[PDB]
């Protein structure tokens, strides 16, 4: 129905706004673009499903997300990819892991404050009807 298409359009507006607020934070610069094959040719042999915030905006606009739960699966993949690729005790690995961690926790805290639970449940019930 047109009412259901207005629901998904409001979801996309909400997801674009959260993603922009993450992408401008200086801590999260390393998560804003795909890893460069040249600089790191090993990355795509270890990490089987790369993800970054530029790819997330493109996915919003392609109508890939019909719920906030499916958006958060991609934010969780950004933060699990960085934990798995950079697991060592040295300062450079520890700095990306504390930050990858800060990106996950910040996304979940904005959603807990600003997403209405009944809006999410509506999106879930429209998705489950299709
Ligand atoms: C203060 C530096 O930042 C942190 O310690 C943030 N948390 C992590 O790195 C978690 C515990 C972790 C560690 C490892 C070895 C593998 C997967 N996750």
Image (tube, rainbow, N blue to C red):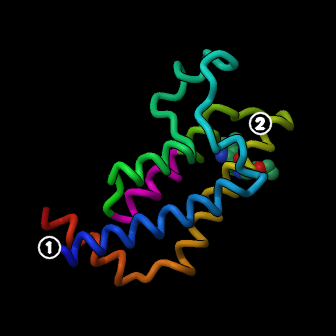
Q: Position of residue 69 (x, y in %)?
A: 39, 63
The numbered disc on residue 93 is: 2
Tell me the distance, in whole angstroms, between the alpha carbons under discs 1 and 2. 49 Å
Q: Could you tell me which secondary element the residue under label 2 belongs to?
A: helix
The numbered disc on residue 91 is: none
- Say left or right for 71 vs 40: left
Query: Is residue 57 within the magenta segment?
Result: no
Q: Position of residue 50 (x, y in %)?
A: 51, 34
Binning the other alpha carbons within 10 Å of mark 2 as few (below 14), some (14 to 19) or many (20 upward) gives some
The answer to whether residue 106 is above or below residue 51 is: below
Query: Is residue 76 within the magenta segment?
Result: yes
Q: In which quarter of the image is the N terminus?
A: bottom left
Q: Position of residue 115 (x, y in %)?
A: 47, 78
Q: In which quarter of the image is the C terminus?
A: bottom left
Image point (44%, 53%), residue name: 73
Q: Give the range drawn in magenta.
A: 67-77
- Mark 1 highlights which residue? 1
Viewer-side residue, 47 vs 111? 111
Binning the other alpha carbons within 10 Å of mark 1 as few (below 14), some (14 to 19) or many (20 upward) gives few
Confirm or reject: label 1 Cβ below 8 Å from ligand 1.
Answer: no
């Amino acid at each position: 129905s047109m009412q259901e298409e207005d629901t998904f359009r409001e979801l996309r507006i909400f997801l674009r706004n959260v993603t922009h607020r993450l992408a401008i934070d200086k801590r999260f610069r390393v998560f804003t673009k795909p890893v460069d094959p040249d600089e790191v040719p090993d990355y795509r042999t270890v990490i089987k499903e790369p993800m970054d915030l530029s790819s997330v905006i493109s996915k919003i606009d392609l109508h890939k997300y019909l719920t906030v739960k499916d958006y958060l699966r991609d934010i969780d993949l950004i933060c699990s990819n960085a934990l798995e690729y950079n697991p060592d005790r040295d300062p450079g690995d520890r700095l990306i892991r504390h930050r990858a961690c800060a990106l996950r926790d910040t996304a979940y805290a904005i959603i807990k404050e600003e997403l209405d639970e009944d809006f999410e449940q509506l999106c879930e019930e429209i998705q489950e009807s299709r």
